Amino acid sequence: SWEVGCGAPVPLVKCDENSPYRTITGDCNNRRSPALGAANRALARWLPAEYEDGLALPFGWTQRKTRNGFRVPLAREVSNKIVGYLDEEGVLDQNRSLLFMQWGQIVDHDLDFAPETELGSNEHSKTQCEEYCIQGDNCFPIMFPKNDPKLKTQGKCMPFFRAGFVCPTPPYQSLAREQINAVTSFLDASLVYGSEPSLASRLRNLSSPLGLMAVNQEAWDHGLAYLPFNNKKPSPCEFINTTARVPCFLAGDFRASEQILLATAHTLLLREHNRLARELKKLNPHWNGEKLYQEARKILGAFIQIITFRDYLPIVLGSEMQKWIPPYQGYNNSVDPRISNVFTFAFRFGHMEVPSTVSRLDENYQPWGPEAELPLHTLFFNTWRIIKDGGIDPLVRGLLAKKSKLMNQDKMVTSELRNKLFQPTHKIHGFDLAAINLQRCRDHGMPGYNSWRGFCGLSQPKTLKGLQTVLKNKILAKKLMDLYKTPDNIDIWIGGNAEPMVERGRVGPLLACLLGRQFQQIRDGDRFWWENPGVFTEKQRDSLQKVSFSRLICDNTHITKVPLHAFQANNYPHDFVDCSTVDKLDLSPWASREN
Amino acid sequence: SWEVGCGAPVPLVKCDENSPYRTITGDCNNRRSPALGAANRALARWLPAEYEDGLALPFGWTQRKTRNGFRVPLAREVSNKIVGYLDEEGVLDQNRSLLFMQWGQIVDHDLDFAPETELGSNEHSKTQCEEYCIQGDNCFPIMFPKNDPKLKTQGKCMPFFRAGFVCPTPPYQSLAREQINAVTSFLDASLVYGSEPSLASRLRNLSSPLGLMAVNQEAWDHGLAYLPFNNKKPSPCEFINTTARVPCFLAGDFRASEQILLATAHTLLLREHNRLARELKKLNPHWNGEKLYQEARKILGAFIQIITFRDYLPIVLGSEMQKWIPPYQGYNNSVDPRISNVFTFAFRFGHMEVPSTVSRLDENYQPWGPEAELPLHTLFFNTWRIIKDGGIDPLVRGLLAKKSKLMNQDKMVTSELRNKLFQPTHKIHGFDLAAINLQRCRDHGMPGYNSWRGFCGLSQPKTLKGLQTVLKNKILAKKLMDLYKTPDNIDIWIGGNAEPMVERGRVGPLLACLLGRQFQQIRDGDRFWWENPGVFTEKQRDSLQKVSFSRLICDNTHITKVPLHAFQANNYPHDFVDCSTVDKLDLSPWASREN
Ligand code: MH0
Ligand code: MH0
Ligand SMILES: *[C@@H]1O[C@H](CO)[C@@H](O[C@@H]2O[C@H](CO)[C@@H](O[C@@H]3O[C@H](CO)[C@@H](O)[C@H](O)[C@@H]3O)[C@H](O)[C@H]2NC(C)=O)[C@H](O)[C@H]1NC(C)=O
Ligand SMILES: *[C@@H]1O[C@H](CO)[C@@H](O[C@@H]2O[C@H](CO)[C@@H](O[C@@H]3O[C@H](CO)[C@@H](O)[C@H](O)[C@@H]3O)[C@H](O)[C@H]2NC(C)=O)[C@H](O)[C@H]1NC(C)=O
Ligand SMILES: *[C@@H]1O[C@H](CO)[C@@H](O)[C@H](O)[C@H]1NC(C)=O
Ligand SMILES: *[C@@H]1O[C@H](CO)[C@@H](O)[C@H](O)[C@H]1NC(C)=O
Ligand SMILES: *[C@@H]1O[C@H](CO)[C@@H](O)[C@H](O)[C@H]1NC(C)=O
Ligand SMILES: *[C@@H]1O[C@H](CO)[C@@H](O)[C@H](O)[C@H]1NC(C)=O
Ligand SMILES: *[C@@H]1O[C@H](CO)[C@@H](O)[C@H](O)[C@H]1NC(C)=O
Ligand SMILES: *[C@@H]1O[C@H](CO)[C@@H](O)[C@H](O)[C@H]1NC(C)=O
Ligand SMILES: [Ca+2]
Ligand SMILES: [Ca+2]
Ligand SMILES: [Cl-]
């Protein structure tokens, strides 16, 4: 295969330096080095790649070959013996709403994507991998360990394809494999607008001069907009219920329809851009399509940044917030804005916050219809449950009123994700997200737990007792040692997520470090950061401070009661207030008379 | 596809319908369909695109793949074996001045521009294409044939970048790839004023309310104006002589400084707008900056149209003039005003009319200084030879008194263009304009010779003997067959230009058809055509008939003696008369009292 040898800039660079707007592609943000943070480039490395053969082959590729002396345990064996649990009772997070989980995934999709090597080329090398479990080239199968229930049910393996990667480049230098980030490293609403101008154009209402995003023309949510349907086949959203035959939504990000609440959040964000465009049309009738789009885009861009840094990261990082993301001291153009390879695994802490069910709630936040509570696994690539069952309002009430799953050392990932995950190109609700994470760490040539512990100036346990100490759990440490033999070999994803959460936070000290560092860098290293002088007026920045997720819902649904702080656990009706009481985004400071 | 929806970048501006002036962008000319003829749209297709893969990839992309059975020959091999010649003796056109050549290029640049995917000169992918000759994406290298002298001197290839294309500006294809026309399809002096309002504003003297175009403030031509300097770096005009360090001129068209006589013609046109503005200021003191600019612009607009249709096209099309451009029957709003893809190659007949030298002539039309006669290749992106060596007057005398090169089946393109062309982003006087033309036909998915022969209801030869008959040349036909194998595969540019010229014209029957059709359409389809009732008064149209290139020179240089008809071969002194004897543009009919 060797898909994408390189990698050279598909969209090139057109650095119009007097432009006050971000490029779609993230190009020209850093003037010294224009390609920093741009889409379809190599993920940054904070540490060098670690491969079996020093180059491309992941640890666990060759049966014989070991890692610091010891064999690497099968991903799925780690999943079963550490990450699995049966009893969904008492697992919910008492002080975080489901929106906490959902916003994590929205942010993640803005920041990074490392899609599978793109070509089958009308080929059965896709099925050759899946059907016959033959390791080779980009087929890197997850092998089931002995006694795995799925041996009886699914055969020898789950299929897995290695992430795409950059050049054999003209020097043809001996180089480590570097995975591509297909989206813009900047927090810039790229999941709404796209990370490539082909898509970004295709997503716009251009037949109208109002700088509107294209909306669905086949269905409506009580007069409120849905995303257009992706009519490209084969559609996995139609596959999951062939009777309903409802396609996936077309969005700025490839993964928008991956699960119903993600599609829902994508719907809120789209409605908000169009709401901003027709409000700026009233204030500035002389402004043309491009100007409305770009200003709406810039505002939405800043909304995501503010909600992320003011509301979201403080409750992720807790006691470590000020240590890693201090108060803002302005655009430092020598900071690397690019998303690191390791961050893409660090931010998968989200996977342990996803509970087993999604609720639809009515206008009194009571169960909506007969089947209010749906198991998560039925909502993978599910657009019909939106179009043909009540719109997004009942789902949005669910996000405010239901709880995220709490990370728990004895109950890590729900079987809805660990056993019943649906992958868009395969036929079965039978995959393991946790196994995929461990396999993917290896694919990406991830350094081990201690390598990253070291990188964060934290202790590097070499012993059962030393690990017991860091994890504050004897049975967990013992299980990890039985499988990995050394904490050096522990795959970063399970290692970071094994660490007890920090005070007032929702991740361990190691992930706090890794997340904190990256979030500091995408702020400080962003020339279009919202707080950077000259991006917005002082007037505009005063008005942008009032924004809230609560207000987003009010302005873009038919929901009237919302809580003041949407990310904390809020029960109806005590913790809810009327939409009329919530501060608004006053757009007066955008009013451009005598232009 | 996104078909019926596909749209690329554009300013998306609305229509002030009561405006009596052209938009900068060509928007709102056609009221039914406002975008027709506007800048930064798809070139029209008269026949469907023909690509290797039916979509985007040009014929000659894949070494393997063939065209109607036969492989397509390397562009450079066609250049060397057909288009080249050594002997510049007797090649001059004895009945056309050099202004004939120069006016062609001026008109061309008003009408169409399909710029390369714009490289920022900040990437390794620019040099990756140039240095390693690696075909991929927008790098489509011109490969040297074996025994080509440039192998020893320049490596394996000339670099070549594919023209930009619509909706997706990076690669996505389901409908055929359509190249952009970055200028206004209307004959409207857009090369003076710009095809985009950011530029058009930036080119004006706005700090004075006299509707003047900005002029050079660093240098003067015996008190007469030069265009401002293009401050954008790196400047290729200062690259060609780093001691002189003289930048390229800033004009309405990107290509103004491509060669010294083009820059010269751009200088005359600019001086004439300013001369019109300060004459209309005298006649109408109450008129403001906008009104002076727009009326000056409208007059100059009409000048170019009249010289083109009354003087230029008759001597291009000869016997075919009346057939294709009959007498004017008024604005037909159902005619397509857009420039076709194929026209942009048809109008490159100009390339075979460019002679090997440019002369500076003194006040007696004698050699000016010791180095009067300069080889053409030294005058690519050459502004210093104007600023620091005599101004434009000696060069303008050259245009009147020297001859255009004659198209010749045995002597097609001078080595000045065929071996020694300079490209603005590269370092060497080493490119081949003919090779680039053949490569560019393929890039633009051009149908073959016979496809266009057919489109013009002319015979479609399938044999050596049949081709010999059409070309009235045995050795040319034989060479074409040895390379292309079928006349079906012959690239439109070399095919049209191979055809013996029509009676008292300067192109063959095929180009007569293609040029004639397009010129008919940009007249008939233009709502602001100068002869269209209501654009000008009957009085104004009577005064506009007197204009001449001879008069333009008189009013805008320090030249005193000029011929009555500048496009014919005119020798000093018999055919020259005094400037006082030439009919003037009487601007009395623009006098607008009591407004
Ligand atoms: C708060 C963060 C977060 C949340 C919540 C989250 C929630 C979910 N996830 Fe998942 N997810 C998160 C962060 C990621 C990241 C960072 C990546 C890696 C992306 C990349 O390629 O760079 C990821 N998730 C990657 C994935 C992948 C791809 C795995 C691979 O091939 O390696 C899948 C299938 C996926 N998720 C599913 C889901 C589903 C389903 C949900 C919820 C129902
Ligand atoms: C009578 C017409 C005419 C004349 C004379 C003429 C004279 C010249 N030329 Fe050239 N040229 C003419 C008509 C064109 C056209 C129509 C185009 C295509 C433009 C477009 O993008 O739509 C063109 N020339 C395009 C070009 C290009 C771009 C080629 C490519 O990349 O595909 C170059 C470099 C160029 N010329 C050089 C020159 C030079 C140098 C001279 C004279 C000194
Ligand atoms: C692109 O934008 C244009 C307008 O900016 C959209 O066309 C507009 O579509 C709306 C429907 O969304 C139309 O309004 C409708 O009027 C009927 C008739 O009374 C009513 O049944 C509906 O409730 C609705 O109000 C409207 O005709 C039309 N506006 C204009 C100016 O044409 C177009 O749909 C957008 N396209 C995309 C892809 O988003
Ligand atoms: C040299 O160039 C000039 C181009 O202007 C040519 O002179 C012109 O020749 C044309 C033929 O295409 C003559 O057209 C004729 O016009 C008269 C009108 O009185 C008409 O009776 C004829 O039917 C014909 O249409 C034109 O008179 C003549 N013009 C001038 C000013 O001399 C000439 O043909 C070229 N010579 C060569 C050898 O190519
Ligand atoms: C939940 O967290 C919020 C802010 O993170 C805090 O103000 C509140 O006291 C906490 N409440 C509970 C019940 O944990
Ligand atoms: C599929 O869709 C129909 C309505 O479109 C619905 O009644 C049915 O319950 C769905 N089937 C499943 C498996 O959920
Ligand atoms: C920018 O960040 C670097 C660390 O990469 C730091 O050394 C430097 O002090 C910062 N620059 C400024 C001006 O604060
Ligand atoms: C503006 O107008 C004045 C007088 O008309 C003139 O001196 C000046 O050169 C113009 N400005 C520019 C930049 O050309
Ligand atoms: C370069 O420019 C200078 C004027 O600055 C001129 O005298 C000299 O002859 C030029 N040299 C070349 C090599 O063109
Ligand atoms: C106007 O345009 C159409 C060609 O598209 C043609 O059918 C019609 O005859 C034209 N009218 C005139 C007067 O040429
Ligand atoms: Ca982004
Ligand atoms: Ca034009
Ligand atoms: Cl065409």
Image (tube, coloured by chain):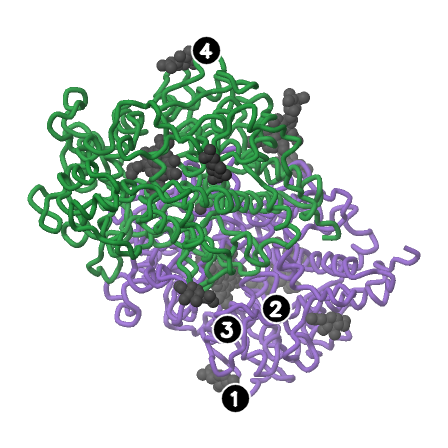
Chain colours: A green, B purple
Eye-nearest disc, 4 or 2: 4
Nearer to me, A175 or A268: A268
What is the chain letter for disc 3? B
| Above/below status of B590 relative to A270 | below
The answer to whether dots 4 and 3 both sit on one chain is no
Q: Residues within 10 Å of mark 4 (few under 14, many from 20)?
A: few
Q: Secondary structure at mark 2?
A: helix
Q: Is residue A538 left or right of residue A215?
A: right
| Above/below status of B238 relative to A295 | below
Q: Can the viewer see residue A495?
A: yes
Callouts 1 and 3 close, C-beta under 8 Å: no
| Mark 1 and mark 3: Cα distance apart in space | 23 Å
What is the chain letter for disc 1? B
Expressed as whole percent of the image width and height from the top left, the position of residue B302 reads 71, 56
Q: Which mark identifies residue A370? A: 4
Q: Residues within 10 Å of mark 2 (few under 14, many from 20)?
A: many
Mark 3 or 2, nearer chain start: 3
Q: Can the viewer see residue B457?
A: no
Task: Report the number of discs.
Answer: 4
Q: Residues within 10 Å of mark 1 (few under 14, many from 20)?
A: few
Q: Secondary structure at mark 1?
A: loop
Residue topped by disc 1: B370
Residue topped by disc 2: B265
Q: Secondary structure at mark 4?
A: loop
> Farthest residue in the right direction?
B594
Nearer to me, A136 or B415: A136
Residue topped by disc 3: B237
